Image (cartoon, rainbow over all chains, first blue to last red; front, top):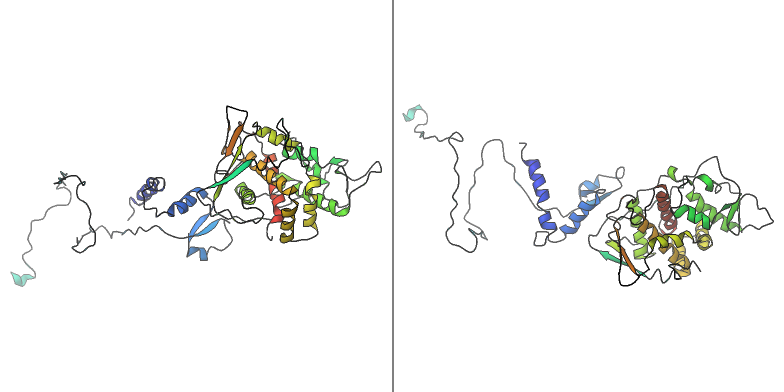
Length: 132
Length: 281
């Protein structure tokens, strides 16, 4: 399903300096030290706690049992078939509609064409021939 | 007694060692390196016989970045265990005017050391980030050799600033009948514990090699700046983040325009004189 995957990688690699250099971040906060190390060393290879058990001795004498992964679990789409969402009713928290200074919000928005995903008006009226 | 550190004004190397500041910073570089047997790599079948000096023109020619005249095997008279040394520390194979040689242990130690220094560009010395790590390790934690867990900056204040003259009154400084008993201790198979006791006690060589590792890092770093407090003759000069932003020697011709093979000399130096402090092979 090759894709914006690499572009997404590069974007998220960029969207951390706005977090690891400035304050007010999800750095929580030690990821700073770990990420600064990883960015400043170039020599060590950082292996999660599993792989280190296998990388024994005969390579780069520069490594470390890294841990404390960043928590971002992203889903993967199936084949070209589309995706459906089942917007919920149960929750514990809320999200804001238009900025906390104003009433009614209006998202004047574009539209899709008809040469894209079409519109069928054919109403399926029959199963097997008996129903006729 | 070691040398009056000159500035146009005398010194005793002790004021000039308590003159500085070594202050740490953020970004713990949890990157504890490991030592290494210092790769003596001695060999060649073409020596220079005669009276080769071994103290002052020796140390100057080798570590003062003076003429890079190929500075080769001339020390190769450090193999051949039957050579001798005359008290002025002239290494020879024929003591001419009835002059006397030193006792044995002294000879063994001195030959050991210069033997380690013989033939650089055939030595396979380790990359320099690690040697910077060990140097700052020593001069920060002391002779205990705990890993850094941080990073360090060095700053000097008030010198009639002449770091070139620092390197100079190095050029004029003797060391052999200062570090002889130390390598003597390492020759007859003592152990880390007692030699650490020794270096703690005597403290004449402690100050010396503190200064020496300091000078080599300030000569091989590149995060270096200087300034003169223009109200008096007093330079403050700093070197910032010594171990993270340095991977090769320097060429900024504003601080100390340092060549190459003498730089690998210097790293061999700090390697081979910090060797006996640390743990096993």
